[PDB]
Image (spheres, helix red, strand yellow):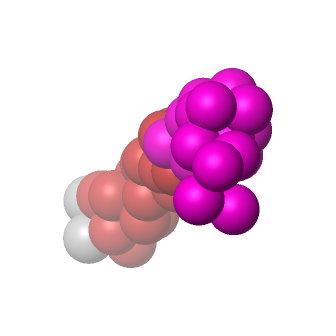
Amino acid sequence: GVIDTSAVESAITDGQGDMKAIGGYIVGALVILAVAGLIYSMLRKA
């Protein structure tokens, strides 16, 4: 912690803050992979 809130905030920006970055970065890669699906579908179709 309750008293931490202060120092906790800092950790929140990193942990919680860095969390959002991970979700975005991870999604970025997922999007790239999905590109292959379409490419294959186009080549297999087409």
Q: Where residue 40 appears, x then y in whole percent?
A: 45, 63
Residue sitting at 26 percent across and 70 percent down?
Answer: 45
- Residue span colored magenta: 1-21
Image side of residue 40 versus residue 10, left or right: left
Q: Residue at x 33, y 58 (%)?
A: 38
Number of marks drawn: 0
Seen at 34% across and 68% down, the residue is 41
Q: Nearer the viewer, residue 30 or 3?
A: 3
Of residues 41 and 33, which is closer to you in this image? 33
Q: Nearer the viewer, residue 2 or 8?
A: 2
Residue farthest along the front direction in this orientation:
3
Q: Nearer the viewer, residue 11 or 36?
A: 11
Residue 42: give x, y in percent of width and height.
Answer: 30, 58
Q: Specify whether residue 18 is painted magenta.
A: yes
Q: Is residue 2 above or below residue 3?
A: below
Q: Main secondary structure of the magenta part?
A: helix
> Quarter of the image containing the C terminus?
bottom left
The quarter of the rendered structure image containing the N terminus is: bottom right
**Residue 3 is a magenta residue:** yes
